[PDB]
Length: 305
Ligand SMILES: CCc1cc(C(=O)NC)c2nccc(N3CCc4c(cc(Cn5ccnc5)cc4-c4cn(C)nc4C(F)(F)F)C3=O)c2c1
Image (cartoon, rainbow, N blue to C red; front, side, top):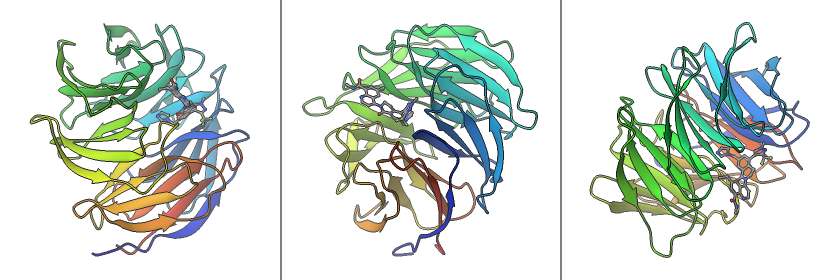
């Protein structure tokens, strides 16, 4: 494919404050959303149909993530906890306590026996899903931690921070294996491993996204044209059709780039505030996007390629 043709299909209204994160379930059936309104909502991934609300955090929620079997969610909240939820019942199975400030970002490992979290308290924590106990506290950064992500076999964690660093961690030992810097040390506002585990995609608050070979410390691709100077905006690899990079933007648009050529191949208009979060469906060419307080809707876009 040369360019996609994403078109708006559904708009999901229901959160009463800004939406902070949207994520598709691994089995493709569901979209989970978190919000500053302290709620998680579940929505049908293909029809946008509202399914249920999951409640329990005492303050707003920054992030949510799915277990590999699509049965559990973990949420990261300003109440300084994470919560593990059984989605079908809505029960809170565990409350993960230990961070000393807002918990901002979270993810399961592929086995989904571990959770990783990052916090305003500048640490990264690794948690046992079964017991809810904190296994390791990493002295990861010297400013708030903007993203945490496991690689494809769970052996590595990548973290990013406003301190301008990206770090790679050994899951088993907790040791810092690599520190990665970039010219003029802009805040690193998002990072995640590529699906094959060989690269990391990193956003910095100089309106720039970069694809890095972290083993060689070499920058392979640079994507620009969007606005990102303030917020920690999710970015994605889109792999179900053409190979794209997808990101939100502070000019209220979803940006889509050709991964190899770095050209902008589509901009999606419709949101009325900053697009803080995007996600890519695991098997179909479907993008979910979510916006901040003046919009607070979620949108589902569909493409033929
Ligand atoms: C590293 C932590 C940090 C540090 C600084 C800083 O230290 N600045 C000097 C900083 N500054 C300015 C703005 C910041 N924020 C704060 C708010 C926010 C932001 C990004 C995302 C999306 N997201 C979630 C995980 N990964 C990405 C969600 C929310 C959020 C959380 N809740 C409860 N409601 C919302 C919202 F916005 F939807 F309302 C975001 O960027 C910010 C964050």
